[PDB]
Length: 114
Length: 114
Length: 115
Length: 115
Ligand SMILES: Nc1ccc(/C=C/c2cc(Br)c(N)c(Br)c2)cc1
Ligand SMILES: Nc1ccc(/C=C/c2cc(Br)c(N)c(Br)c2)cc1
Image (cartoon, rainbow over all chains, first blue to last red):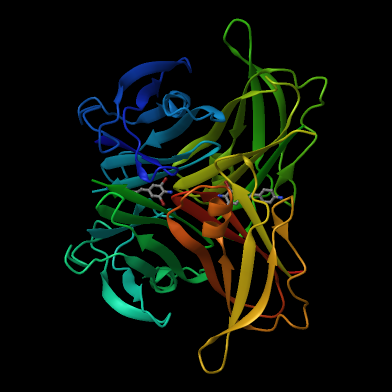
């Protein structure tokens, strides 16, 4: 129900071995851990959740962009990239959060399909 | 060896049924037709060329963004989106040209892999 | 020393009246409110801070994109766009945080200059 | 009435000294040269045209991104970034064409205002 795809705009490649942490907003307004992983060789992270666990709510996808750039010997601007959104059942059922990274910039989009 | 992927930043979806025309630069500096198609339900166009035909050279991928927006009843800025690049054999072998469309803006990136 | 510029990729215009909240990470790892404002008719927000006040730290620039799209009567994907960065850690710099908004997407960039 | 602004997403800076060529589609469907220039230290190029000269038409703004990256001693993917649009077809407007550059990617947006 939830996939993350990360691309590198400097090298023209998937962004491999990027740490990604997903959080769900709790009733007290704290962010609690939900799912995490490292992007694959294809820059993707699948297997984060199941339909059962992925209930409506506010989620945060934190992509560790600073460590990614540092590992490539490149000095970056951001601490991380943050994508915060509401999962809504009246919308399509599969969510892809994509991000396109540069050292001083990033783009993100959502592809929400049925 | 060549794929095109198009996404819609307004609807959060693949951009479906978008016309895409590929041209190769000729020795006289004219653009000659090379391959074309319409994006699928997943916003992708595969099958454009084969490894045999996709030789080094300068290529232009023209995405008919104006017709796409007009069909959705939305007034857009650009006539089309143009992506012009050199295919180089000393680089990885598969090229994905991706574009992310808005009415007054677009993003494009290349994912070049082995 | 800190400016925010926001554009609307749907309308081809500045994004006007966008609320922006800036936080600074405190000693105790919480996010302290630092400054806030709204973009002008030119999509710009200046006057957030001074070079005295804008010390080294980890800053969070929260751009209230959902409130923007909903005030336009549109239902967008993101809650906000957050831009988090270390500032002034090699001395004072001037920062422009720019963002380009669509209902299901945004991009952000930084322009950092040394006065 | 026509301005071009270019930023560098690698350095977090204006993209300076970027060559830009503007064309206008002629009666015979060819691309006639219209104006050209280079971005300044602020990544901006003004003074391309006048409101008299900038008549209705289909215009092509070619940003020479490959020459930029190669002058920096970097090998980029694209030959250039081309921005093609109809202008002034409901009367005169002011156009800003902005671009944000990386070696394998770019984004472009337009800001259109009615003076
Ligand atoms: N499988 C597959 C391959 C490539 C993509 C490209 C996504 C994409 C994301 C962002 Br954000 C921008 N700005 C751009 Br241009 C493109 C998606 C799925
Ligand atoms: N004066 C001034 C300063 C900064 C800007 C930024 C424009 C801008 C263009 C793109 Br294309 C993207 N993707 C992003 Br983000 C931002 C414009 C005018």
